[PDB]
Length: 115
Image (cartoon, rainbow, N blue to C red; front, side, top):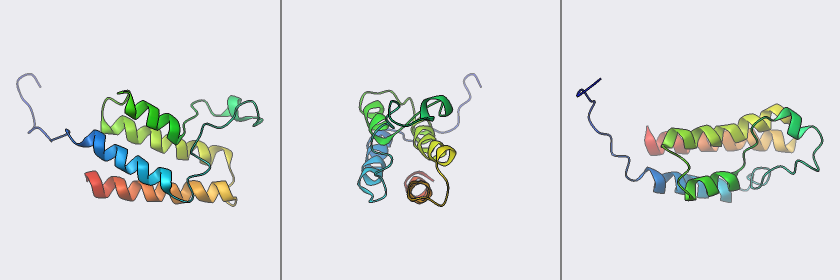
C-alpha cells in the first residue's frame, strides 16, 4: 500500500531474457505454423473465429519496440499463440501437435528462467 512495498525484484534483465526465449521458440523445428501471421484472406473462418490473432513475428516486433510493459504481458501473447492454435486445429493434426509441443517447450523455459 502507500509507502509499504515488498522488496524490489530485479527486472533489468527481463527484456534480454524474453528475447532469448523467443529466439529459442523461433528456431524450434515445430515453430513453422507460428512464425508469421495466419493469412486472413486465404484461410476461411480464421478472421471471424480468432478474435485476437498472434504469431512469433508479431511478438518479436512488439518486444523490440517496447510494447510489452512487463514479462507477464509477454507470456500472455506467447500463450495466446497456442490457445488460438488449439481453437482452430484438431489435436490429431500436424499443426495441433506442433502447438502442444511448443507450449510445453515454452512453459519449461519460462519456469527455468524466471521461477
